[PDB]
Each structure stands twice: as structure tokens, then as C-alpha cells.
Amino acid sequence: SFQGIRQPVTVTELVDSGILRPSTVNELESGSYDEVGERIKDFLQGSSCIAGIYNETTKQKLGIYEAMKIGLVRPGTALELLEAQAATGFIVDPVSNLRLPVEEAYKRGLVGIEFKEKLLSAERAVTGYNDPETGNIISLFQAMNKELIEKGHGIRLLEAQIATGGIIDPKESHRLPVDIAYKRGYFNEELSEILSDPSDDTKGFFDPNTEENLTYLQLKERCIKDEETGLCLLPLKE
Amino acid sequence: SFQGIRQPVTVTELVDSGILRPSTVNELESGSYDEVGERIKDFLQGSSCIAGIYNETTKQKLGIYEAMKIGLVRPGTALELLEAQAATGFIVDPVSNLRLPVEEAYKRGLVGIEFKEKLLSAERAVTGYNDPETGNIISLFQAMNKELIEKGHGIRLLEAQIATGGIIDPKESHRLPVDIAYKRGYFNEELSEILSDPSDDTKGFFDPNTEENLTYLQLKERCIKDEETGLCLLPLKE
Image (cartoon, rainbow over all chains, first blue to last red; front, side, top):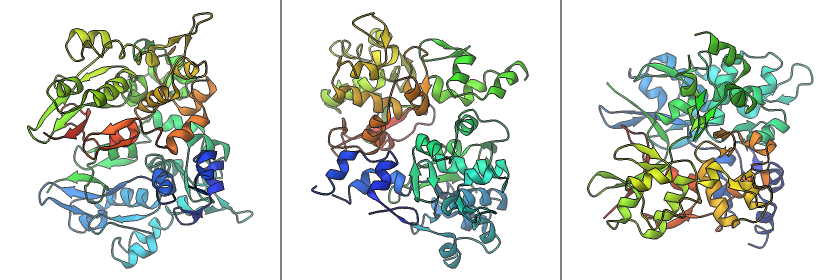
């Protein structure tokens, strides 16, 4: 029925997901559909992330890669935002307002050849990883529980997702309330505590201006919204 | 130890609350406290609400009551924002940057004599209502389950709270993760669904500009942040 990150989402799947109320279905059959998917938008694909940069100097908006290609953000911090962009679904171009998978983005010149390989791994936190035994699609979380990636790197991707609608379901392709995420084994309370009560390890992202470390949630709120796009933008200088 | 809405909050109470990790406690004996309460701020008192107004005309920021006293917001919508303010803990003065209980606000001239009685009831969704038989402090939720208030009015206050840190615990005086709120009988999934999938019913609040109905979450994102205060402000005109 509705459009998810990659795959379409069934109306049943969302009601089971604790997203839509049993009544709103009896209202779709004998009702609209462009408004329902408009009321439950943040779950289908998610809310805005740090789409681009906006430097006070020229008053222009820029993608993340373009700004590092011209010296306004060191290659280092560029990777983080472009990873958190991948881990939520799509790479973004504020100028044109495009949202696209790593492969498309690379064709369109929105991301470097040097970054492409890493941005192709952080996107598996969207479409799923693979189980060494069984070859079955498992969650980023289940991938941390089987030791296929560092808890610092994995944790950094989970907060990018939680700060833009909730943790994603690999199989169903959409955002999920924290409780359902717990029921389906894709997150837990031990992890919520690490974000609510951050430490010096969980300071994954770096703020260019104030030059300090913080969480996606924290950095994201340091951003300004755009009117014709809505995409949150990180203000910079020089 | 930490400061809550009204009452102080024990370090045990927060760990039980699924808020602080068991390690951060043993790390309170070993070097801070002004930073811990700075990492878990949104729960202690909460995030910003719609504190005031900002009219494009004069470029000034105003409290909600002052704007209706000069004609820039009809008495009707004034009540909504001043109720949602009460139901989150404190009434707000963007100009001076004060946060205060209804009683103090009324002395200070931030709210009218006509509104005082209603703003004194919506604050019970903060400090608790009273159970007829046994006269014990019950949750706003429990007050809805015993028919002491309309589900439309009660629902409108729960979304004001959820959009600013989470539902509040009357007894403990702080915000709570949705799952704990469920465990303690202060919310449920049947209610999350009404917010995630909102209707013409759960549209409680009115936007003066676009002139339409929406949820606190939606209206709040239509707001701009302030630099010296951080309080979200609702932009208007005339």
C-alpha cells in the first residue's frame, strides 16, 4: 500500500507495528490515501536529517560532499554526516532537493569515489546485514550482538536513526516505535540508556563551529530548517 | 539529588526509570553532577514548548498573554497554548526568560485573572489529580480511565507532554520513556496510535498563520528557536 524506505508497506504491517489504529483502516476502505501517508510520514521514510551545510559567508546551501571539495569541512567530519545520511535511507542534495541511494548518488556526483565503499556498508543498517550462518537478513542491532561491527560505529548509526523517526526495520522497511523495536529484537533498554545518558565514547559527531563532540540529536538541533525544502541545514563559516 | 519539575529526583529513581545507566552512578562518586543533569535535562524538566510569539512586524518576542491583550491572538487560541504550558510544568516569559508555576505567573502579570482557574487544573497533569475514594494522587491517564475529564481535553494535554520529553510522572516529578510509562500505568499503546495516526479529533491546536488544526508536535515544528533563550517561538503578523 504505502511507500517505505525501499519496499512498499502493507496496511496490516503498520497496524501490527502499533502505528495505525484499527479504525483508520476501515476508513481507508470506505473513506483518503495521500493524507494517511501524510499523517504517518515520519515512519514511512523518516524526518529530516542533516541534509547539507549553509555558510553565513555566501548565504548558499551546500551538500556535504561539495563543501569538503571546496574546503569548509574536513574530510573527517564529512564521512560522519554522509554515513548518518546513508543509515537513514538516502543521500541528500539540498540545492536540488534530491533523496537517493548510495549508488544513484555516486552517479550524480553527490559523493566521492573514495567514500562510496563505506557509504555502501552504513546503508545495510537500512536494508540489513547478512548472517554468517543461515545467510539471513539480520538487524544492525543483531549485527552488534554477533560481533560483526564495533559498538562505537554501530551505536553512532542507531542514534542517527532514532533522531529521525525511530530505529528502522530491515525486513519491513520503515520506522518503529521503541517498544515494537524491543518486541522484535531490534533494540533494547540498555541502549536507550546510552543515548539518554550519553558519555564520552558516545560523542560520535563533531560540530565544526563550536568545535566539540555530541550526539546526532544534539547536533541536529544545532541546525536551521529551510523553507522551500524543509531539510535541516548545519550553519558554518569561511 | 537532581531537580525535577517540582520535587527533587533521587539517583535510584532515575536508574529504575530506565534513564541513567548503572555505571553512571558509580561514576558520580568519581569525577560530576552539573553535567550529568545536563546530559539528562530533557527528562528532569523537559524540552522547550511554545513559550511565546514573535511577530514579523515589530521583530519583538512576546509571551502568549501579552499578545492577546494587544490583539495578535484571539482569546481562544491563547488558552490552548497557556494550557499546554501548564501541563508541561511552567508558564513562560520569553522576554525575561522566566519559567514559573501558575500561582507565581499570575502575581507577575504573565496570565490573566480570567484564565487562572483553568490553568490551575491543567497543572494537575503535572502534580496529580485526586482519586475520589482513597483520595490518592493518580495520573492524568488514570483520571481519563475513571471519567474525571473529557478524552479530548485530556488527549490534548498528553500530546503537549509527549512532544516535550515524554509523559510526566505525578509522583516522581520527571519525564518517562514511553515503555516505563506503560509499565507504571500512565499511558498505553492505544494512545500512542491516536497521536502517530492523528485525526480531525486529535487536532486540538490552531495555527494562526495558515489557519488550520494540528497536534502540538506539528504546531511546535512550525516554530523558530531563539538564540539567547532557546525557547521555541510561534511566528505571527499584524
